Length: 296
Length: 258
Length: 8
Ligand SMILES: Cc1nc(C)c(-c2ccnc(Nc3ccc(C(F)(F)F)cc3)n2)s1
Image (cartoon, rainbow over all chains, first blue to last red):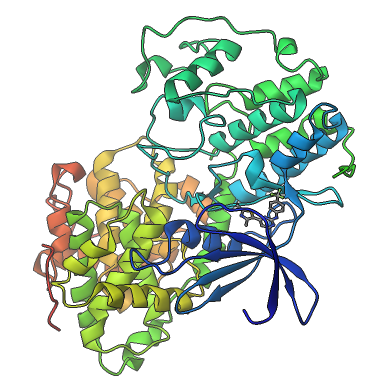
């Protein structure tokens, strides 16, 4: 720990304080996430435990690298490769003029790659959202913040009281089934896809129930045709307004026909039919993909 | 899950290799003994149930313990501690919320202290170099269970129970990979309830022909038969609950037709 | 159950 020079703090999150920091012997610039460990109370957090063990296992160009973990008596340091900012900022700052299609397309492309590496190692991310998606100037994007991810060698039982995120949350969790699935990560990513495009969030809910209702208003109230089995899910109410599904052309104008097909396959109600990440990549939307750099 | 399944199943097989105790570990521990470890896992079962914990948790716990004991001499006074921290950790890894540390201290008859349990957590992490997502039997049973035709709760609960039973006796269960034990347990449970056998779907997926199981299968049978008399009982207890269809009641076959 | 100071 004596080998790093803290430079400047670059965001909070799970546990504590993340620094930009530089290795005084090698010049390498890193991101230190320093976890508090006055832990008179429960010891190493569960989030730390997961993000470390899983990241350890995952090595792929669109999943932020864990470089080292530093164990003291009294503090726990995670050392990550340094990347510049996070998709949330890029968007705020790119607002007005908007993020060029081709860059959107590569960001999506690049994420599906990482999601796919993740999913195909029974890791479930669970909290994809711009702030947890990290970009660099060479124009790569990467999965980050794995503090809630989970290994699914056995189905992953659902958080009865979810402290996660509303806006990116899958209908099927909203309606209270028992398990997660790879499908939830696709959802959050479809929602981030539509965000990059329209320059605003797709389903800005104000509580579990308002969420459902926003989803429904865009995509139309699910019934048993679309989603065999909905009407028998713990939180499903027969009183749910029966809104009709809107022409997607209406929801993401800027988007070519392919973009809409993908987007819809990713935002399918029923987790059995919502498109896998491995699939999405074959999608023709990705025919003409390049790798532009962002103007940061 | 219908897409990676194979990728996953492949990777667990890869992982289970790297996450493996050493077999000889118990005889190189000065002060402790296969017995001693039995007493322990047994105890974990019981904690498992008291705090109502997912089964995987317990499978993890033992796996951590077995690797922790494969690098580190421990004295018998401190085993229950290693176990407590192994359990804490796995609960932290696999449960939605885990028991507080206080409870874990409580459940030992405050034989150790919060700061003791917390210190060991750390050492345990240190020693596993943080590698916690170990494949377990209970994972491969769950992968295996897809290939029933058709499904059958008794069978599942039975295979489970045999699974956990393997947890208790380092001899000879440490010489087997979980994917194998999980097969074994699967064929036995199948066999026992419905007289059917380890299916071609699974033989083709797993590369394990029946005959390749036989070694592991045999010990497991012997175990199934002897469990009512085994020094250690918390599991049989556990697997009486109607939650598990009374399967630990059912009558073991005396022969396997091998 | 449970509460137990395992003697070895
Ligand atoms: C939460 C996060 N957890 C990790 C591991 C984080 C991380 C890891 C590595 N690099 C970075 N860089 C970074 C760079 C810029 C920003 C910001 F805030 F400016 F956009 C935020 C984060 N962030 S943030």
